[PDB]
Image (cartoon, coloured by chain):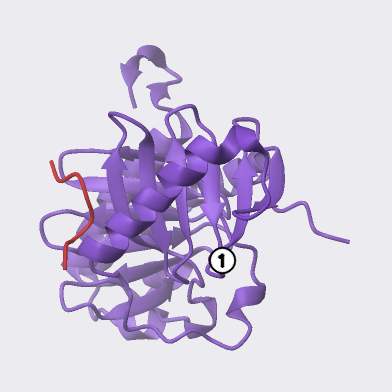
């Protein structure tokens, strides 16, 4: 009965579509409208259930450890495998480089995963002791736990941001300096903006094009388009030696 | 660049 989950190729289709829609929003110059009505673009029914609320870049040794906003934890290891620990303290899911998923438990698991389990526990403990939870102000909706828990598909960092791409399609961009964050959902064609005051607001992209938005959000969306391009192909299709 | 998300 279990769903196989949205497959990565299907995620890539929606990503390309979001790339195109970001281009369209951005080319519409949304901060230049006669009267910007950003509030009218809000779409509360499309609020994301999941985002990365904490992260640790130990990629020099092991990988990128993270917490999701339901307090589950995961790691994308340097061998492109993922281990996630659900918020019950014991349930695990292991995802191989090719996406093959297996379910296990901390109490009952193949011995082959002992090392990666122990590393995940170290990441968890670190995050819990040291790091602030992003979106700690959002109270979950009833049944949000029924949505498929995603894993971190890919990530990268620039000088100004970290880019986190989840297996449900979402692309999260966290800006280092000012703590502002974007959560782009290519399935809902929506974007959530977390501003410097920690206000969390979810917009329909097509409505940002219709109604406009402030220049800070407009600026972050220009950068987002560039990040999506990089995600889709780290190297340019017009010159594969050149970084997207 | 920072090696973690925002600290407590």
Where residue A175 sits in the image (x, y, percent)? Answer: 20, 55
- Badge count: 1
Q: Chain of mark 1?
A: A
Q: Nearer the viewer, residue A187 or A132?
A: A132
SS class, disc 1:
loop
Pointer 1 residue? A188
Q: Nearer the viewer, residue A72 or A121?
A: A121
Image: A166 above or below A89: above
Q: Please identify the quarter of the rendering in which residue A94 is found.
A: top right
Res A28 seen here: no
What residue is rendered at 47% in x and 35% in y?
A232
Left/right placement of residue A131 relative to residue A187 reads left
Where residue A107 sits in the image (x, y, percent)? Answer: 63, 55
Crowdedness of circle 1 by 10 Å Cα count: few (<14), some, many (20+)? some
Q: Quadrant of the N terminus of chain A?
A: bottom right
Colour-to-chain, purple = A
What residue is rendered at 40% in x and 21% in y?
A236
What residue is rendered at 59% in x and 30% in y?
A97
Q: Nearer the viewer, residue A155 or A170?
A: A155
Colour-to-chain, red = B
Res A167 seen here: yes
Where residue A88 sits in the image (x, y, percent)? Answer: 56, 70
Q: Quadrant of the C terminus of chain A?
A: top left
């Amino acid at each position: 009965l279990g769903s196989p989950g949205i497959q990565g190729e299907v995620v890539d289709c929606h990503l390309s579509d979001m790339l195109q829609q970001l281009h369209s929003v951005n080319a519409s110059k949304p901060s230049e409208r006669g009267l910007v009505r950003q509030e009218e673009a809000e779409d509360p029914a499309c609020i994301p259930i999941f985002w990365v609320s904490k992260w640790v870049d130990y990629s020099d040794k092991y990988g990128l450890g993270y917490q999701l906003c339901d307090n589950s934890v995961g790691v994308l290891f340097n061998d492109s495998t993922r281990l996630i620990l659900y918020n019950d303290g014991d349930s695990l899911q292991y995802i191989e480089r090719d996406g093959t998923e297996s379910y296990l438990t901390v109490s009952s698991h193949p011995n082959s995963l002992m090392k990666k389990i122990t590393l995940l526990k170290y990441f968890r403990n670190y995050m819990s002791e040291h790091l602030l939870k992003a979106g700690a102000n959002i109270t979950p909706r009833e049944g949000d736990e029924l949505a498929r828990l995603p894993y971190l598909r890919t990530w990268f960092r620039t000088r100004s941001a970290i880019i986190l791409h989840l297996s449900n399609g979402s692309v999260q961009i966290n800006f280092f300096q000012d703590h502002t964050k974007l959560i782009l959902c290519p399935l809902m064609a929506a974007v959530t903006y977390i501003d410097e005051k920690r206000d969390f607001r979810t917009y329909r992209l097509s409505l940002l094009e219709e109604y406009g938005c402030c220049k800070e959000l407009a600026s972050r969306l220009r950068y987002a388009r560039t990040m999506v391009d990089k995600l889709l192909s780290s190297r340019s299709a017009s010159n594969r030696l050149k970084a997207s | 660049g920072p090696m973690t998300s925002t600290p407590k």
